[PDB]
Image: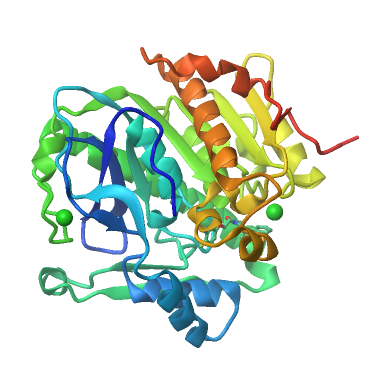
């Protein structure tokens, strides 16, 4: 089981696609909801996502069917299409998934943030970095739910530099576009969700605190954080969770005016990657870095909660540290950073110590030596 948020709000969840095309925005929303008795949200909602995951892992598409059999009725504790909690403007987080992931696999993080009073828009990227995603080829296909699927693009070695950069820039634009969509919806622009879901988007009118916007992401999504920030001044800070820095152009390192927090796993990182993180540092710019002791790269995503301790450790979904303990540290450090850099009037400053790595399960800065 994926854990419930620790904050005082109930959390709801829905999906938004607009427009219906492969250049439109596709996101999963997590939001503070009213009390309700709605069903929990289906974690991986389509069989095609499991086929995509199979391709990502480099196995037979038949392994997709086994993953589906195993994980396909699993839920995450957000209430599907529950009404939005009225009477408050919420800060907004745009969330970017990793390579071979997709919008639904960072619910542990999304739910927790929402439970403390954020709206979270988890984008699904159409750069062919998602294991799978979908769109509709025309209006009629949208109306009848006739999906067209795009699966992960596998690259030759020779393409990696150029295409990964292409992808991160597209990811950035997708983050910007998703923000613009939510801002339009906030202002009251009618939006026809290409998904025909029973969640009225008019609820979100006047629900967004328009100036308090952050971008957060895992691995590829962490590089996405940095690109988005350099390109789009509406995002006031970023949190990169175990950023994979490789996709970023050399030009961007010196072009990130906003506060930026690096939260790393112990075992993922390596000098080449850390050096690039360090290139973002400058005495006029706000940067923090911590490393979660005993943690692995997948501690930041939901599959860390999907298996037992032994199978999970063997698969590198779990580290030495307990997955709940790890994500709690990342989530609370994140909340303190956000309160400080969006100017929130909450009690997240209670975890200010975590930003400085001041906890028995954290390492201030990094364990990686780079001299
Ligand atoms: C491919 C990466 C990598 C780069 C260099 C070396 C090693 C790995 C870059 C990247 O974005 N990564 C994160 C991918 O996270 C995922 C993928 C699929 C999932 F189902 C879930 C879940 N839950 C999470 C690792
Ligand atoms: Cl329901
Ligand atoms: Cl790892």
| Total numbered circles | 0
Answer left or right for 59 relative to 280: left
Of residue 68 and residue 252, the one placed in the foreground of this image is 68
Quadrant of the rendered structure where residue 347 is? top left
* Quarter of the figure with the N terminus: bottom left
Q: Up-down: is 173 above or below 59?
A: above
Q: Would you say residue 173 is visible in this rendering? A: no
Residue at image point 39% right, 37% down: 5
Which image quadrant shows ligand 2? bottom left
> Picture coordinates of residue 36 (x, y %)?
16, 42
Q: Up-down: is 147 above or below 359?
A: below
Q: Up-down: is 305 above or below 21?
A: above
> Picture coordinates of residue 370 (x, y %)?
86, 37
> Picture coordinates of residue 140 (x, y %)?
10, 73
Q: Up-down: is 363 above or below 28?
A: above
* Quarter of the figure with the C terminus: top right
Of residue 364 and residue 25, the one placed in the foreground of this image is 364
> Picture coordinates of residue 313 (x, y %)?
67, 60
Residue at image point 81% right, 43% down: 271
Quadrant of the rendered structure where residue 203 is? top left
Answer left or right for 225 relative to 78: right
Residue at image point 39% right, 42% down: 4
């Amino acid at each position: 089981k994926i854990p419930r948020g620790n904050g005082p709000y109930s959390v709801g969840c829905t999906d938004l696609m607009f427009d219906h095309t492969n250049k439109g925005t596709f996101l999963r929303l997590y939001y503070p909801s009213q009390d309700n008795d709605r069903l929990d949200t289906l974690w991986i909602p389509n069989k095609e996502y499991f086929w995509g995951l199979s391709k990502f892992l480099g196995t037979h598409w038949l392994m997709g069917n086994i993953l589906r059999l195993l994980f396909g009725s699993m839920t995450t504790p957000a209430n599907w299409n529950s009404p939005l909690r009225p009477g408050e403007k919420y800060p907004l987080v745009v969330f970017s998934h990793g390579l071979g992931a997709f919008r639904t696999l960072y619910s542990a993080i999304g739910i927790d943030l929402a439970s403390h009073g954020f709206i979270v828009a988890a984008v699904e990227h159409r750069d062919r970095s998602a294991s799978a995603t979908y769109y509709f080829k025309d209006q009629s296909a949208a109306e009848i739910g006739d999906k067209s699927w795009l699966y992960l693009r596998t690259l030759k070695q020779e393409e990696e530099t150029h295409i990964r950069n292409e992808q991160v820039r597209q990811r950035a634009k997708e983050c910007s576009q998703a923000l613009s969509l939510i801002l339009d919806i906030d202002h009251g622009k009618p939006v026809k969700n290409a998904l025909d879901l029973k969640f009225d988007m008019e609820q979100l009118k006047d629900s967004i605190d328009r100036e308090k916007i952050a971008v957060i992401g895992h691995s590829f999504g962490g590089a996405t954080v940095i690109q988005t920030l350099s390109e789009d001044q509406r995002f006031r800070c970023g949190i990169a969770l175990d950023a994979w820095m490789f996709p970023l152009g050399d030009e961007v390192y010196s072009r990130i005016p906003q506060p930026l927090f690096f939260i790393n796993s112990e075992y993922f990182q390596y000098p080449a990657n850390i050096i690039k993180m360090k290139k973002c540092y400058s005495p006029d710019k706000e940067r923090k870095m911590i490393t979660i002791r005993g943690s692995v790269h997948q501690n930041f995503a939901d599959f860390t909660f999907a298996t037992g301790k032994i199978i999970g450790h063997m698969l590198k979904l779990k580290g030495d540290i307990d997955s709940n303990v790890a994500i709690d540290l990342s989530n609370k450090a994140s909340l303190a950073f956000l309160q400080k850099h969006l100017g929130l009037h909450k009690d997240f400053d209670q975890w200010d110590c975590l930003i400085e790595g001041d906890d028995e399960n954290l390492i201030p800065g990094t364990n990686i030596n780079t001299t």
